[PDB]
């Protein structure tokens, strides 16, 4: 309501003004020539009893 | 006519040179002749150094110059650290800032 | 035959930037507007210069700006945006001779480039674009040419052409492309700068686009005045994929 | 808004840094703050070397 | 520690070809970090007899990127491990392997499992569970190195 | 380097008129008035015709 002088972006009350958000998460992932489970990929598999 | 003339002009950076030793906390600087006429209130200036990586002090002009070799600035602008400006250091303009 | 384990979790990190206001104006008396000059219209000439200055200032601000917020002379907030150098903190070095400066060799340059390829991130791939000055590009070409294992081969006679100009550097991790920045070439010290980056990680966030503004001279004054005004800022996503270099290359 | 923001997270190794020297027979380790929350009962850890 | 030169690298590589093993052959697979691969390329490029030949002008491309090393007894193929790249110290490690000599023994495969929360508890819980093992046949046909840098 | 396969044959020397540098290139031509003068022969003027 009453604020000394003209209104600015710092003049709203609590929580009246939200800022701008990018509503997601940017993921950083390891980079390489081989797959992530590189040693797992090369092997063959045999069952055990 | 036996005489002929033409005109040329170039567009470049707005670069200034300090002439006197300036300690930290001194808000008035001395430059070369007529070099202060090219800056107005609201200009952002940076202290140069060799190569790139200009992470140096930033100044702001806070008052329109009245002489061609004097400048009134605010030191440590934008959260930088005020430091001693040597005799022959150059200064370059990197933009403009204004309040709402 | 044990039970299931306990759980654990973690949270992301947050980043910020501000918007900045840019203004540039021009003024001329009404008498001078009517006068005829050999060079041409004075009003039209001034606007060209002021546009050049405005664009140059915007570019420099997005390269060397620093983030801050304060209270202006009228009690209202004053904000400045931060450039690439502000966001790039992991990968930045100063080449040269002296304390705190790394000596520049081929191996040092190779080591400098290797760090930007550790994390894939998003869309980064294995290529980068670098902006350099003429001095830096010449130094890189000389480094390639002066290498002990490099030769230039002629058949039976020197003929046709001689020299050097290459713009592509190949590394085991990735690849770099070089272009020159016109604003870097003009300045002496700025010609020794190199800016490697991936374009997918940088965007421009604009609150008010650039706009002309007219008739701002004092009321009752015999003159013409104009202005340009805009408010906008910079966003950088994955700084680990970018680097900034100083010194002769 | 004159202010904008974004979030990022990175998938990487789980590392902890010791803070005080530990003898060969002490079962409690001091680490940097908030790092101990990452581990739970049953985890296998190994000492790092250059 | 052993000082690293091209001759030291060759001597390290040579020791895995003395025995034929389980039909291993004359080829091996190497998993490295970025730092080790860069050092190997630098060692190859700095040899006194190596030459890079432009015709009339240094014009198009410069640099180095190769992944095969030939020995009088065999050859090695390189490939960078994503987990080694991230860690500062793991990036200077090398693994020489014979893929036909390493197998994974599985008792129970990985399976999602749901509804692990306590009865009458107002939450959701899930988990992953498995049981695996590793078998390596001829350990003298393989090698491990660290701190290549 | 100037290369011969197994033996020098059929030609030798040097004649080229283009210099290439990262910024641009230079083309060389000889001025007849410069050639016939001793001191003027060691002169080079690079110019933009337009």
Image (tube, coloured by chain):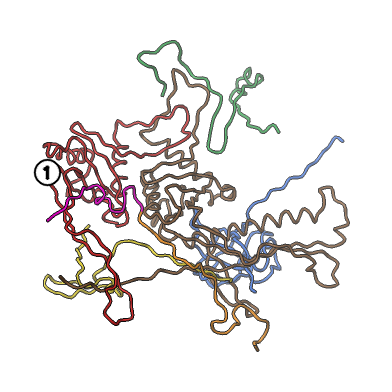
Chain colours: A orange, B blue, C brown, D yellow, E red, F green
Q: Which residue is drawn at 64% across and 87% down?
A: A3
Mark 1 lies on a secondary structure that is: helix
Over which residues does the magenta segment extend? A31-49
Q: Looking at this view, is E134 or B4 the one in front?
A: E134
Could you say which is closer to the camera, residue B42 or residue E56? E56
Q: Residues within 10 Å of mark 1 (few under 14, many from 20)?
A: few
Residue C162: percent from left, percent from top: 50, 28
Above or below B70: residue C138: above
Q: In which quarter of the image is the N terminus of chain C?
A: bottom left
The residue indicated by pointer 1 is E140
* Outermost residue to the bottom: A2
Is C64 situated left or right of C49 in this image?
Answer: left
Q: Identify which residue, C75 or C103, lies in the foreground.
A: C75
Between C82 and B12, the one lying in front of the other is C82
Residue B86: x and y, percent? 52, 62
Residue E149: image location, x then y, percent: 27, 49
Tell me if I can see residue C241 in this picture: yes
Total numbered labels placed on residues in the image: 1
For image coordinates 45% across by 15% down, the residue present is F12
> Can see residue B76?
no
Q: Quadrant of residue E30?
A: top left
Q: In this view, does E58 lie above or below C1?
A: above
Q: Which chain carries label 1?
A: E
Is C213 situated left or right of F13 in this image? Answer: right
Q: Above or below — where is A32 with respect to C70?
A: above
Instruction: Look at the image and say whether residue C149 sits in the magenta stretch.
Output: no
- Asked if residue C8 lies left or right of residue C25, the reply is left
Q: Position of residue B29 (x, y in %)?
A: 60, 67
């Amino acid at each position: 309501a009453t604020i000394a002088g003209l209104r600015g972006t710092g003049d709203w009350g609590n929580q009246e003004r939200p800022t701008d958000f990018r509503e997601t998460i940017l993921w950083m992932e390891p980079n390489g020539q081989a797959p992530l489970q590189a040693l797992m990929s090369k092997m063959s598999s045999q069952p055990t009893t | 006519d036996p005489e002929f003339s033409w005109w040329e002009e170039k567009l470049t950076h707005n670069r200034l040179e300090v002439k006197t030793e300036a300690a930290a906390g001194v808000t008035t600087l001395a430059v070369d002749t007529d070099q202060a006429w090219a800056c107005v209130k609201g200009d952002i200036l940076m202290v140069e150094s060799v190569g790139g990586l200009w992470a140096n002090e930033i100044l702001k002009v806070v008052e329109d110059p009245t002489a061609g070799n004097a400048l009134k600035v605010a030191r440590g602008f934008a959260g930088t650290t005020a430091a001693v400006i040597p005799a022959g250091t150059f200064i370059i303009a990197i933009g403009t800032s204004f309040a709402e | 035959g044990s039970l299931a384990p306990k759980s654990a979790t973690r949270n992301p990190v947050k980043l910020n930037n501000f918007c900045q206001i840019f203004k540039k104006s021009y003024e001329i008396t009404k008498t001078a507007d009517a006068t005829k000059a050999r060079t041409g219209s004075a009003l039209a000439n001034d606007k060209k210069r002021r546009m050049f200055d405005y664009y140059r200032d915007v570019e420099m601000a997005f390269i060397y700006g620093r983030k801050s917020e304060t209270v202006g002379e009228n009690g209202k907030p004053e904000r400045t945006t931060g450039g690439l150098l502000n966001f790039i903190t992991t990968n930045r070095t100063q080449f040269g001779t002296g304390a705190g400066k790394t000596e520049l060799t081929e191996d040092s340059l190779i080591d400098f480039f290797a760090n930007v390829f550790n994390y894939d991130g998003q869309g980064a791939g294995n290529q980068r674009i670098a902006f350099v000055g003429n001095t830096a590009l010449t130094k890189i070409n000389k480094l390639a040419r002066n290498s002990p294992s490099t030769r230039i081969n002629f058949d039976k006679q020197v003929t046709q052409v001689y020299g050097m100009n290459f713009t592509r550097w190949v590394l085991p991790q990735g690849e770099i492309f070089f272009k020159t920045h016109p604003l870097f070439n003009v300045h002496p010290e700025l010609s020794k700068a190199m800016m490697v980056l991936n374009p997918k990680g940088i965007k421009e966030r604009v609150l008010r686009a650039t706009k002309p503004e007219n008739d701002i001279q004092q009321v009752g004054q015999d003159s013409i005045k104009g202005q340009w005004i805009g408010e906008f800022g910079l966003e950088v996503n994955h700084e680990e994929t970018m680097a900034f270099a100083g010194g002769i290359a």
